[PDB]
Image: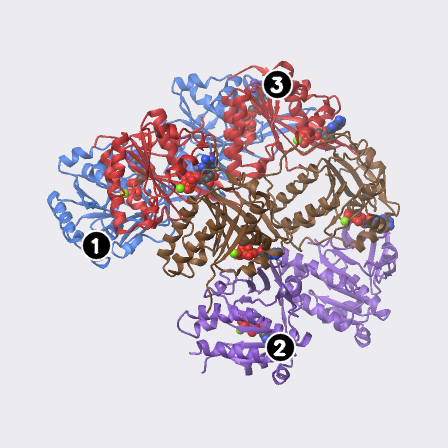
Chain colours: A brown, B red, C purple, D blue
């Protein structure tokens, strides 16, 4: 058989939930203040109408209907229309400053029938315990509401507050009663930085993905969940070769970089990583293909000034409309946030080539787990969209395991030689091509890079 | 008495090994756990297996989920539900206030005693004893205390489920670990770095022996609860080929058909090439080959294989090759096994290949991985299949090593102005092998393993 | 939701505009965070920046004290009291008034026609009462009528622990719309002031903690460092090095001199600051290792004269200790002195000293924040770093090394990295004397 | 000895307790549910009535006398017969679904009736639950110990705990049943439980301080292992299974010796293990193999290849191969097992392949404890012990008597292997690094 589920509209949740929220049942959304219990509730009712024309009811035991509307309107949600259309109904159960319980419970049951709603929200189920001191009576009344909503065949979602993030499901023993489905939101503080996370603890009779998943409440978008579990090892590959910007490196790769590829350029500082990047993006704009560049080290001025000395004209291509130097700081937001910005501008720009510089900048202010998840998540999409990607990783050991993902590993190192700090290049991997296995000496000028001959008496330096 | 505490088996996979036979018969057992630990599933499976295998009718007393819901919830598992209920095989007694606007032994004792008598049951489940408290204290404890005695006299192997607040803390809510102090089974679902892991444990069995500690399990759909007792886990001179003939000579004839081979090295060394040759060997002779990729897409695998001179679509069309392809983060290792064991059972392969294990190491803890490789190597051995595992050495510039029969090792080597490669068969049980580190060249023909280094 | 610029440096950045206008915000924090000060800044800046009358109420302190406590900041608050820009309703218990005190508060708002308002310690009320009926009176008019009156309110509240509940007496339950958390985290034997906006129901904000500091002549100075490289070369101080660095250092460049002790890193800072003062340019030396005494003779022995640089007002030695405070506290003094000095060049000797007195992030945060300020100010910045990762943050890198040759430790210099220029890629011998550095031939 | 102690008969307690339980006073045996309070308490009575002819009385406030008889059966004591013989008396103080003052009188009479020298009150903590008088209960409990003291009986008074490393016992029974306190623990560490026993205090007498390991074996019960393990050594030599290595050692290994075979992967450590074992079975001796890496199938293939039939040896009862996973149990539970098999097969030689496999599933602390325990046990039992360790090339060193070092080494243009005896306490040893080869006839050193 199959437990039926109702798509939420919060794309990503439907993947994690394997369809949606069990229909005709109550789902408990628990979270500490600031998580996103209210927003999550409207999207459930918003898409409910703006897709399946399923009427919904919002019972607010806290914030005023007027404020609710104002708060939610910034997400581009015209709910005042749905109200006038008779799709949505906001029931004001918030007490006024200037039988109360049992009366409101029935005044709610009126709205569920009047609008004949299938997607109800009881916002702040905890706020009813912080209002009716007869909690014993409240609990008994809430148990009835759940059974009533069940008999009425409504897919309910009742929000609940928590005191601690990694502590109890919810307060006021609200874990029980509404205990068929339990979704937990969190906002954990770690390293003076916050991380919104969503978890589905239990689905009675249904299946779901198990664990926390990063989410974000984006303005003019809403709750955007991005499951790395959804990532499917089903990317496409081709034998079509692009250019690197350096014809010599293209010969060393046996024609050039494959279009459907991820290239790693490893090396110490001052080796010439942010050079092969410029040539990479330059090679695109030259052929008319659109390029990108997410800098996490140098400003546009510096990037352009560095590039102007090498013969690459950025401002031209930037204005011509074949380049988009994003440039930001790794410490500004978080990896989960950065990933969204990258993914956001990609679809907009529709780039032929992407280029991170560096990944090490990002790794610094993260975890070994967080960095992995980021790297694993970002590489996949690029390969899914068939966008050629170059990634820069510094070697703090001047003279992570991202190489497992990358198809091409280009190593740039320094080589001391008779009072002369020379430079060496080698292609370590090409995945699907013949590459030159030779450690060639190269030199940088205002002309670019000149990959020369091997060191012959090459002191075993590389690797 | 002179009655050694008999252990009635429950069928549920692993528990009967962990419980040294099964649940103590003629007694109650506490299946405690926080929300979503799989107590309801555990309880039903106990009953279900009862009525099917041992033909012992069972009664299910619910104090939360309505009978109709329970039937629908346990449906996807593929167990018969209404088929059994509509035959006096199973009985779901409801004690959850069906309505409200109402207000003991009236809604207990006899109701269950009747059910046991009516359906002639030998197994019973009391779902959520903790629910009684929320609904209806010292009186409730008395009734529940008498129920354990009544059920003992009636002679029924009972399971009494309860809830917990914390995973690593008090055994059960409302000190039910006193009313049903005798047999305790703990189910836990621990956070563990944003990655939930289910586990099962028998804290105590009064009068009998049991496997101590936490054992992992999974609540799969078409199956139910499956516990993996890595503890419980407990013959050929036929030499098979590798794909590379000179590597076979390095092994002294080839690989044994009943063996696990490890291939370790950094990226770009040529582990995937050896995999494509390993499988090609099977497809050539007319054997079957299964590949589990966790790193490269089905396309890229084929592309890079075609460049080496190895058509897989030919073999995949022949039905001698199958490629899985799945990111490790898709599910957990506990579920990954279940799937691997499924396609092996179905495809009935000769050679297997997991490329790579190192990709699966990132979606688990050390303990979780070690338990995984033990389970996979065991299954592969039990199914009489040659196996090749691959691992990336964090050596760009163990456990499997101890389990694997052959350890092949790939490495980069600088040759003065050139970056070369080298193969070495570090170990091979029950054969002479070439103990030298040797240069090899990758080409559009394959792997030309050549002269040794010094 | 509209926002009203607070006027607090850095908050309007993190708050993405300001505080939800016409809505109350909760400034929760433990004693000694800066709740009382933050509240005054709001009412203050507003009045001055845009005549928006405000009423401060105090259930704890008394106005005569409050005025004097905020006098150092340089806010003529008496004038506001007379002209009727600011008010101070003393609801502090006299060494009842459930409706009385609040009714008095409502009147003042109507009288002065206040747009801003502050309730200093909404917690105190609970302590300075009897029944928790205060909850009603707080979720009453206090908030509701404030919304009806259309005033942006700040309800200050106390907390017990830094990383615990949002408030003491479940004050959040009432003021549950917008919340701001101030903290004094301690950790180590130093203390860290950080500000976080946990919730702006309806609007967005920069998520997480952000460093802030109460300076005696400014107040809360939140630093949201989360928020034009020229081609004019300057002399390094040593001519051979200038040639090695392709004519000299870019004015918009971060130079990193790296090496052991005895290599000659402080020789190259002395030369660096010297070149500025020579050509009438300001130079500020941040000393973490050495002292005004050690430096003076160290320079004199090399043949530089800070004596006349002190007379000319060209050189400026701060000279402090890394363990005086955390890294957050350090940058302030330099950030301030820079404005007072207008430094063409500036140096930090050393950074390894500061790196020892904090965690990786603390250093990282300092590194990034330090580079920016001067980078966004047009001034050449040299950095000394002892070698027992600003290698990727720095533009130019100089590597000094001891080389053991023939049982006679020699000295060697090399420019490893320089963005935008050709650098000399030879490892040159150098000598030290009473004149300075003598960069010679390579090995 | 100041105060008199009564031997409990439990294996190990009498050692750690320096005699037994202080006689004429009550002892508290506290622990979380499933620690083994009841079993411990019964073995106390059982050995009393049997070995020492001291009658015992069991007072149960939880489990039914009938159940106790059934639960305590597999251990193999005829408790039912001895209840009839007038030695044992299980007082049913268990509550009925539908006054402690009188209940105490019932227990008091039983002691005087049977002339009990030993008494067990099971779960005092229960009493506080069953009867919610609190103060009234505490008083009667204080009167119980007072009365029991006068009649000169040695009492065990059990109590439940919540947390393992938390309070001594619930309901502060500590205050009443002070004087002597024993704590049983069952700690989950790495998804693996650890049974421990500790004498926190003995007022008046000495005892071994700290936790000690124990187990509950189905056919024996509580078996405590005083890790504090008084020996015998001689110039009696024994074979290694390889004649050249015997000559390298100086006429074979010493008998009572711990040998270590360290080396890289594929050197030949398991080979030496297989020969070491054969060296016993081929020279009329018994061998134990604790395999923590290879399965049976793998151990056989290696043996059959090198020309050794372990099956015959096992059929003739000369060899025992355990085969275990390091992750199955904890290392403390692993030793207990090893000791258990030794005290059954009574092996002349013992081999563990390998210690490095055990190190994976244990902390440095735990590994040391294991290595120390195993070494000390083999030497007190006077058995010849070999151990293998995987070393980088592809602390037992200090404790071991012999160190054989296998290594990869190039020579005449060939990557070959070599052996080197590094240590031999009480003998010359060839201090030369000799190359060797492996074949179907085992090792060949040359
Ligand atoms: N219009 C908006 N634009 C951006 N972020 C918003 C918007 N509205 C709310 N948020 C974010 O959502 C968070 C939680 O909002 P809400 O769901 O109302 O709170 P809670 O989950 O505590 O009930 C806020 O802290 C804020 O960061
Ligand atoms: N029919 C089903 N199909 C798949 N997974 C199921 C099914 N029923 C339950 N589960 C899984 O089992 C988990 C817990 O099951 P359940 O026994 O209801 O929990 P508990 O006993 O803790 O209340 C659910 O969160 C879900 O992941
Ligand atoms: N005009 C130039 N002439 C010669 N070399 C230059 C020139 N501009 C830059 N370089 C070289 O480029 C190096 C910096 O390369 P870049 O890719 O920016 O460094 P990174 O390896 O940190 O990414 C400098 O150290 C210098 O050797
Ligand atoms: N057609 C080809 N001709 C020559 N060399 C190739 C060809 N295809 C791949 N190679 C080389 O062989 C290597 C084998 O890569 P692969 O086996 O996928 O590495 P790994 O198993 O370590 O992930 C490639 O990285 C590349 O250097
Ligand atoms: N006039 C001042 N000059 C300098 N620092 C001040 C001044 N007033 C307050 N501070 C700083 O702020 C702290 C008190 O801040 P305040 O807002 O009064 O405390 P609270 O947040 O507990 O109400 C002092 O300990 C000091 O660090
Ligand atoms: N007859 C038996 N056979 C085997 N093991 C037993 C037997 N009786 C008890 N045990 C062991 O003792 C444990 C329970 O010990 P018990 O005496 O009940 O302790 P407590 O009273 O502190 O709960 C069981 O879980 C099991 O490990
Ligand atoms: N029949 C055989 N003939 C020759 N050499 C063999 C034979 N069987 C095994 N070997 C070699 O001996 C090795 C045995 O190593 P082993 O005893 O398992 O030690 P380790 O534990 O260090 O791997 C094998 O790896 C292989 O190189
Ligand atoms: Mg809400
Ligand atoms: Mg760079
Ligand atoms: Mg349940
Ligand atoms: Mg591979
Ligand atoms: Mg204050
Ligand atoms: Mg110095
Ligand atoms: Mg007991
Ligand atoms: Mg071995």
Against C97, residue B422 (above or below) is above
- Which secondary structure, mark 2? loop
Can you give x and y, in whole percent of width and height, for residue C389 in the image? Answer: 70, 53
Residue drawn 52% across the image and 61% down it: A64
- Which secondary structure, mark 1? helix
Against D289, residue B27 (above or below) is below
Q: Give residue C363's quadrant in the image.
A: bottom right
Callouts 3 and 2 on one subunit: no
Q: Which residue is mark 2?
A: C53
Depth check, front residue: C154 or D75: C154
Callouts 2 and 1 on one subunit: no
- Residue C407 visible here: no
Q: Residues within 10 Å of mark 3 (few under 14, many from 20)?
A: many
Residue drawn 60% across the image and 71% down it: C38
Q: Which residue is mark 3?
A: B320
Give the number of marks.
3
Q: Which residue is mark 1?
A: D141
Q: CA distance from mark 1 to mark 3?
A: 77 Å
């Amino acid at each position: 058989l199959a437990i039926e589920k109702l798509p939420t509209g919060i794309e990503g949740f439907d993947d994690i939930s394997h369809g949606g929220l069990p229909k005709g049942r109550t789902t408990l959304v628990a979270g500490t203040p600031g998580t996103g219990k209210t927003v999550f509730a409207m999207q459930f009712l918003y898409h409910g109408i703006k897709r399946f024309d399923e009427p919904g009811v919002f019972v607010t035991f806290e914030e005023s209907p007027d404020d609710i509307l104002r708060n939610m309107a910034s997400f581009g949600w015209d709910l005042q229309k749905l109200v006038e259309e008779g799709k949505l109904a906001i029931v004001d159960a918030s007490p006024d400053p200037e039988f109360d319980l049992s009366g409101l419970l029935a005044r709610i049951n009126h709205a569920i029938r009047k609008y004949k709603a299938k997607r109800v929200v009881i916002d702040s189920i905890t706020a009813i315990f912080q209002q009716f001191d007869d909690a014993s009576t409240v609990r008994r009344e809430l148990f009835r509401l759940v059974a009533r909503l069940k008999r009425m065949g409504v897919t309910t979602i009742m929000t609940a507050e928590r005191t601690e993030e990694y502590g109890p499901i919810a307060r006021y023993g609200v874990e029980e009663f509404v205990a068929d489905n339990v979704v937990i939101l969190r906002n954990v503080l770690e390293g003076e930085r916050r991380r919104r996370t969503i978890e589905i603890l239990k689905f009675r009779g249904t299946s779901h993905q198990k664990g926390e998943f990063p989410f974000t409440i984006t303005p003019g978008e809403g709750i955007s969940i991005f499951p790395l579990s959804a990532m499917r090892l089903k990317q496409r590959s081709s034998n079509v070769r692009v250019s690197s910007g350096v014809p010599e490196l293209d010969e060393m790769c046996g024609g050039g970089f494959f279009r459907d590829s991820i290239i790693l350029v490893s090396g110490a500082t001052g080796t010439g990583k942010t050079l092969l990047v410029t040539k990479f993006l330059e090679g695109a704009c030259r052929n008319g293909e659109r390029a990108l560049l997410f800098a996490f080290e140098e400003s546009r001025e510096q990037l352009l000034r560095n590039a102007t000395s090498w013969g690459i004209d950025f401002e031209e291509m930037e204005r011509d409309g074949r380049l988009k130097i994003v440039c930001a700081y790794p410490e500004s937001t978080g990896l989960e946030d950065h990933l969204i910005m990258i993914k956001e501008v990609i679809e907009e720009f529709k780039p032929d080539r992407i280029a991170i510089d560096s990944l090490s900048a990002l790794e610094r202010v993260a975890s070994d787990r967080g960095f992995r998840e980021f790297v694993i998540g970002l590489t996949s999409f690029i390969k899914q969209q068939e966008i050629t990607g170059l990634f820069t990783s510094t070697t703090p050991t001047f003279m992570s395991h991202i190489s497992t993902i990358t198809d091409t590993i280009i190593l740039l190192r320094y080589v001391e030689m008779r009072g002369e700090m020379s430079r060496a290049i080698n292609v370590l991997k090409m995945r699907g091509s013949w590459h030159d296995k030779e450690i060639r000496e190269f030199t940088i000028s205002g002309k670019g890079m000149h990959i020369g001959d091997p060191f012959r008496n090459f002191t075993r330096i590389l690797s």
